[PDB]
Amino acid sequence: GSQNNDALSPAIRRLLAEWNLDASAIKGTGVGGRLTREDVEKHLAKA
Image (cartoon, rainbow, N blue to C red; front, side):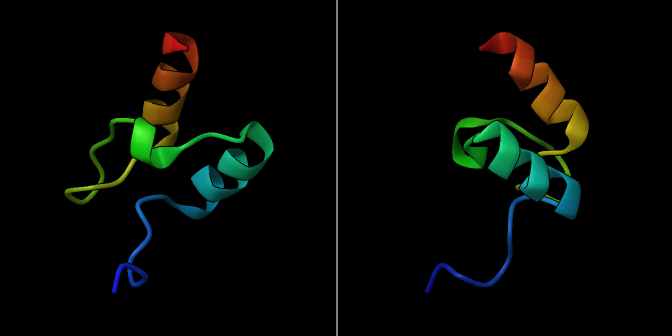
């Protein structure tokens, strides 16, 4: 269904857990639909 490919990497997944962030609410550009450390940091400052 929806489970197959994650929109984040290992570093973003860990960060997401500790930082409790939502990838869906964060813009990125890794492989068509993924947010990187630069996208999270940028988003981290946005809100």
